[PDB]
Image (cartoon, rainbow, N blue to C red; front, top):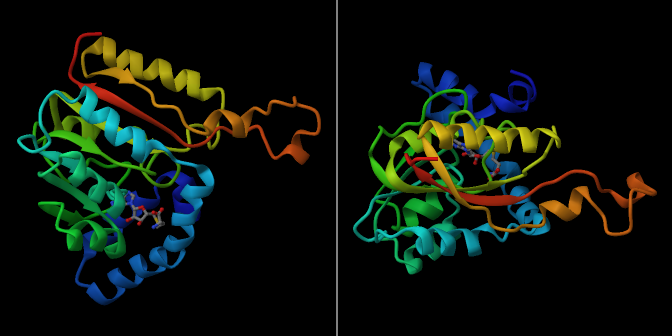
Length: 240
Ligand SMILES: Nc1ncnc2c1ncn2[C@@H]1O[C@H](CSCC[C@H](N)C(=O)O)[C@@H](O)[C@H]1O
């Protein structure tokens, strides 16, 4: 495909391509190309100031009545080694998930924090784990924008049991800035439906990028008007 299937089906392409299989050398090659930029992505989060991992992990435990020790936690391809290392110290002794880049997998798997990690990118297709599997899931830097199509996230929720916790972070408004409010309304519909109930939304640097204290004036010279980086935690299956 081109441009990761319009900056949406990127990962989804991998499941499509991995279906053929029987190509460990090239399958690694494709991932190897992704990992080429990978290091450039790491520094990118620092520039974005994704506090999520710090507050995100803390917030989950604060709202997570169950112990990550006895509960089964889930992490996605965006389960950066450090989040897991912090997760372990946080009190998570049980973790499962899926990741696309071996380098991303190496931190998690080689770390020895994740009980079981699986290679398999996706996005416009269901998550690898089954429903009612893990008591909670925590992914960072993966959303509708070629990485993890926001419709698929709810699949992660599906693999999460009721009363569980789902934690995610990425660019809130990479595009469709007004759609965020539309997006927020969508969560409420799911909450109302009973699928999941929004708990809290942790602060980030997303507001400042789109809106500047000075004003609209010289907007282009201000390099502002786009909201990015935000974290939030939702409960699994709850009433309104
Ligand atoms: N469902 C999924 N399965 C596997 N990998 C996924 C995934 N969703 C996102 N990813 C990961 O997201 C990255 C996109 S391309 C790599 C860029 C950089 N490593 C980064 O962290 O963004 C890959 O590392 C890929 O493994």
